Amino acid sequence: ASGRALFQYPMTSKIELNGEINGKKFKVAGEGFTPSSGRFNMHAYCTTGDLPMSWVVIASPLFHMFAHYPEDITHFFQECFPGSYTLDRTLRMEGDGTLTTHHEYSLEDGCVTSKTTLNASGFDPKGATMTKSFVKQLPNEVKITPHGPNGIRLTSTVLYLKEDGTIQIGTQDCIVTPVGGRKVTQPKAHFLHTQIIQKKDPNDTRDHIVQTELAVAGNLWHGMDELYK
Ligand SMILES: [Cl-]
Ligand SMILES: [Cl-]
Ligand SMILES: [Cl-]
Image (cartoon, rainbow, N blue to C red):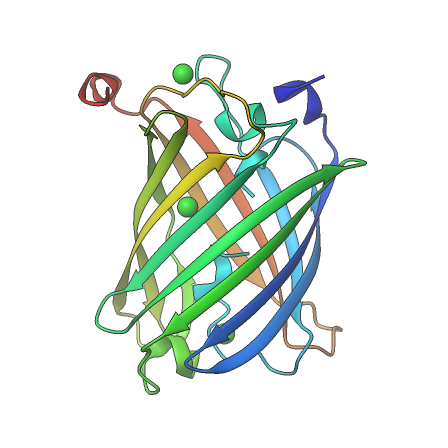
């Protein structure tokens, strides 16, 4: 059983995230549900106190294997199993700071566990990330291309809405690498439409978020694959 055969829904998730921003250390944990392909949630919470950054900015650090892929594009993230992959991210909040994340995953009993680290340095203490002045991030198309002999690269530019109704940009660039000592067939260049919706659980007493991601792959520009060898 491998690949898409291993991703029979419903499934669940867990996360453990160790972080630091501008010298402030913190941790997050969470559990989530994946009812069906492409719709995946996460209820996460800060276990060290209040989160020292925006929940909106931490949303992309908080599971591409749950994306919904049509049959005509390779689902690289799912094809990495068994064996797994790592994700390495850089998120530049333009005019403000840069963070990086590293993710490792394992799959057991229908649950994907993420163990992630986050490092963020140089942020403005009156910026929106540290003052928690974001409301949401807008939906976006992540561009996925073959990268090196055995990985992929994911790139996006994200619009973050502040409380005053204006936008800040985050430039995001990620590399995914199979860690399974085996060759995984690269997909053609394509796009991943992604939306994040966040809310609060009225009862939960912790600093937390309840997040859903909807992620659907498509060959949005059929000529694009020709540019990536
Ligand atoms: Cl927030
Ligand atoms: Cl990404
Ligand atoms: Cl493909």
